[PDB]
Image 1 (cartoon, rainbow over the protein chains, first blue to last red):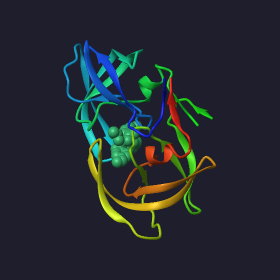
Image 2 (tube, helix red, strand yellow):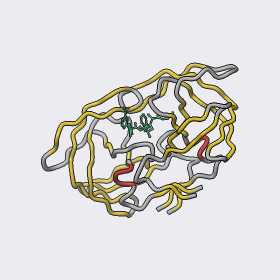
Image 3 (cartoon, each protein chain N blue to C red):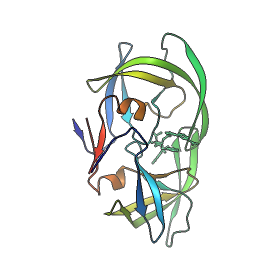
Length: 99
Length: 99
Ligand SMILES: COc1ccc(S(=O)(=O)N(CC(C)C)C[C@@H](O)[C@H](Cc2ccccc2)NC(=O)[C@@H]2CN(c3cccc(C(C)=O)c3)C(=O)O2)cc1
């Protein structure tokens, strides 16, 4: 789809058979999701944002289907204010900015 | 133009004879610029992201040129690491997300 920006670019994602809303976030290097359980090994990581730095858990090679488009990659889980899809997965689903 | 997201979507902006690089950020409701002493009236505001909140100063009707495209609207000025062009201005320069 083409998505205009008069509203937040919120889409439905499927991850581990669960549906969530997440924000398509071109200003985010990394995809960060709110607290949830995912299987497999994770590694402790810290990441910065506008308000300071937070601890997250890093899960690798996680399938997410984002508004119908399949990605498999890194998902950080932690105290993000909202589920964000970052450039690491936006590139996988072919997402570009156009004007 | 079309901007892929392999790297951060940085572009040159102009705000009164300051040229700065800024993120075209679909995950940002509002435009947030690094500390600068803009003329005119402003109001204090708090905005939240990863790590928590920062205090910003909200200026209205500020003309900003983004990649040669004209915009004018609200800009929030405060202690951000990066200049962020938010949805309030992205719409004015005709920016969409596509995949
Ligand atoms: C009301 O208007 C608002 C406008 C913008 C924000 S936001 O910036 O918190 N953020 C909102 C989002 C998290 C829901 C926009 C993101 O795109 C944000 C932009 C950004 C902020 C600070 C530094 C870089 C980018 N992105 C992020 O929070 C993360 C943080 N980040 C990053 C990467 C590397 C190093 C850093 C450092 C050193 O801070 C940050 C990154 O790539 O994405 C909040 C409110």
